[PDB]
Length: 393
Ligand code: HEM
Image (cartoon, rainbow, N blue to C red; front, side, top):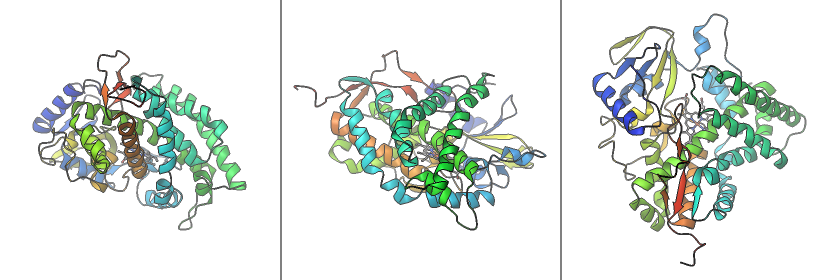
């Protein structure tokens, strides 16, 4: 009666595989309901009326934290997402390419034969880009990175460690008050930055006060950093295992986006999502009571043969793309950061190939560490360049 941890990936995948076949809806000893098949995960994620993103919904006198889009249900979710989206736009994201490329190239250019891909690229990159998108003083970047980094590091710890909430609040409370001051500053004296945009936005009579704007910016950072960090490490780890794709991608960089989707399917940085039932309901004929937590295994869905032929084959030739990418969610909460996630990882892989041709994982480098809670991937990924401009080759 145990959920296998995130680190031993094979044992995890083996267990999910058995669940999809023998117990596709399972109630754990904590009374959390686990959903393993793709069809059923999809059903849960579409049905927001039954499967709420708002645990406060089911509690007398409790209400959601304002600005926290991922914690609220339609109709208000729609109202808010519309406001937020008007600030954080497709051109906003796409104009970021040169800076992403510029930061990435510079960081890699200082990495030679041996290095940790996460320490060098995957960890610092996303947070640099979030800081710049938000428009915050270059002189605030170091502390901003330290707060985000601390919160990434928190996830290395056992999530049932009862000190969890306190250590989270120790970082979160200053972060958000820094952003909320920035919001108030920007409301009085706006610029060309996401915070300014967020405090300037109004869509259908609806705007964000400083509280909402600050909570959103914080959520945006938290959603954006670890996931993106984990994705790039997973990309390199997966090419390591299927290395003929290094050369295919080297030859044709147009192949990179399909590689990024296939890694996302193969190794979702978030293997699980959570909902709360609002009422007695059923999944796949299995009865689930009101007011309980349901965990949808995206990782199990991604490896479901009923949804993906030869699911355990790493195969970028799959006809992937768009809103079908379960690793960014499904339905109204579908990842707001998806274009940025996709952009950052496409540029990152392009740049890795450009400089190195190929990376191999140093699997016996003892600094290698996997996460084991919310995330499927690697905190430190020692690598070895196939080659680099540093060699008199
Ligand atoms: C590969 C990297 C990423 C992955 C795997 C990922 C994963 C996810 C998933 C699974 C969800 C849906 C959660 C739910 O339905 O409850 C989500 C939502 C969200 N993500 Fe991402 N994410 C990534 C990158 C980003 C980035 C870069 C940003 C910021 C630019 C971001 C911001 C958000 C926001 C604001 C939501 C909530 C959308 C809503 O509730 O309407 N994410 N993400």
